[PDB]
Length: 254
Length: 250
Ligand SMILES: O=C(O)[C@@H](CO)O[C@H]1O[C@H](CO)[C@@H](O)[C@H](O)[C@@H]1O
Ligand SMILES: O=C(O)[C@@H](CO)O[C@H]1O[C@H](CO)[C@@H](O)[C@H](O)[C@@H]1O
Ligand SMILES: [Mg+2]
Ligand SMILES: [Mg+2]
Image (cartoon, rainbow over all chains, first blue to last red; front, side, top):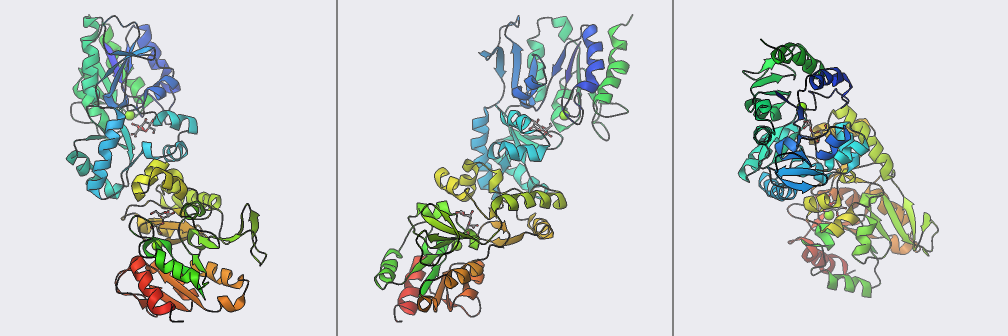
C-alpha cells in the first residue's frame, strides 16, 4: 500500500501545518506504509514542511525522487531527480498573455504579483509567499469571480488547461495529479507495494488523483465526488479518521 | 497667459511623444508663454519626457517647482521644490487595505504588481513601467469592469477619493487637478501673467482642470463638456489647431 495525499485542506490544518496529522502519519510509518504528498504547492513549499521525496508538486507538473531512487528516471535537479510531466512555467506564462489578449480582461497570476501582495491575498507570511511564487510548471491565477467564465474559455482557446485548488484557479499544460501518481507507481522499486494505492484530497485538483488510485477518500467540505469515500470531518481530522477506519483494517487482514 | 496641458491624448500621442505639437510648443516658447504639464503621470515619467518644472503630477497630488522659483513654497528636493497637495502613497495604500476589508475582495493596484506586469497591462516598456510605479500620491488600480462599483463604494467608505484616468481608476486623497492649478496660479511670480489661464485636455477627467482655467479646450473625441471649446481632430493636431485658432491671436 502507498498513500497518496494532498496537502492543503487535507493533511495540513488551516494554518498550513502538519501538527494535527502527526499521529496518523506516525501510525502509517510504523506500519511501513509510504506516504507521498501530491500537491499544488511548489517544491520550495514542500521542502519547507520538512517533507522528503518522493513527492509530486504543482498539480502533477513535477515528480521529485530521492537522488538514490533504485529506478533511474528523470534528470538530476538539486539533490533530487526530477521527472517533468508538464510544460515549464515560462511557457505557461507566455501562453497566458495570449489568453489575456483573447479575454480582453487582465489575467493576473502570482508571477505578476509581489511577494507582499501574494502574502496579503493568501494569508501566508512574506517568506512563505516567496516559496509559493517559486513555480516551475503551474501558475496560480487571481481571478475575480465575475471574470472566471470568460477567462477559462480563453485558457481553453489558447491550449492551456485549468483546475481549481480550493481557493484559486490554476493554469498549466500537462500537469495532472493522476498522470503523476501513475508515473510514480510505475517507477516504484517494489511492485507489490505499489499495487494498492490510496488517494486523499479535498478539491477539484484532486479528481484526477481519485481516478488514479484504488481507494479514494474525500476530506473536503460538502458532499464527496461520486465513488469517493467521505469522512465525518474535513482536513487532518478526516485524514486521521480515514487512516484509522479505512486503512488500518486493510493492513492486517486474514 | 499660462497654458496648462494634460499629457496623454493631448500633448502626447498614441505611442507617447510629440506629434505636430513640437512646432506648436516652440511657437508658445517664442512668445514667452509658459506651458505647464498637468498629468496623472509620475514625476519620474515627466522627467523621462525631458519636461522641466513647473509641472503638476499624479492628478494634482504634487506640484513641482524649480528649486529657484521666485516665490518660496514647498519643500526642497534636489533641483525642485515640491508642494504636496495630497496624502502620501503609503497612506493611500494603507487605506486600500482597509477598503479590501469592507469590499470582501482583493483590490489590486500598481503597488501590488511587478514592473513587468504593469508594462503588459499598460503597453509601456518595462523601463517606462518602472517609472509609472514610482508613485508618491495616487494609486492606479487594476479592476475588472464588473467589480468596479463594489470597489468604488468601499474606497469612499474609508475616506479615499477616486477618478478615472482614461483606462484605469485611480485612488488618492486630496489630488485634484483644479486645486493644483489654482495653487500654482497663486504661486506665480508675476500675477499679471497668471491672470489668464488656458487649459487643454483630451478627456472628461480633465473637468477639474477645465473648471480652474479661463479658457478650456477639449482636444479629445466627440462632444466636449458644456462650456468647453472643441477641435475637429484630437491630439497634438487638436493642440496645434487649438493653439493656432484660440491662443496665437491673443
Ligand atoms: O489553489 C489553492 O487554493 C491553493 C491550495 O490548493 O494552492 C495555491 O495557494 C497556496 C496558498 O494558499 C499555495 O501554497 C500553492 O502554491 C498555490 O499557489
Ligand atoms: O489611468 C490612465 O489611464 C493613465 C492616464 O490617466 O494614467 C495611468 O496609466 C499610465 C499608463 O497608461 C501611467 O503612465 C500613469 O502613471 C498612470 O498609472
Ligand atoms: Mg487541497
Ligand atoms: Mg490624458
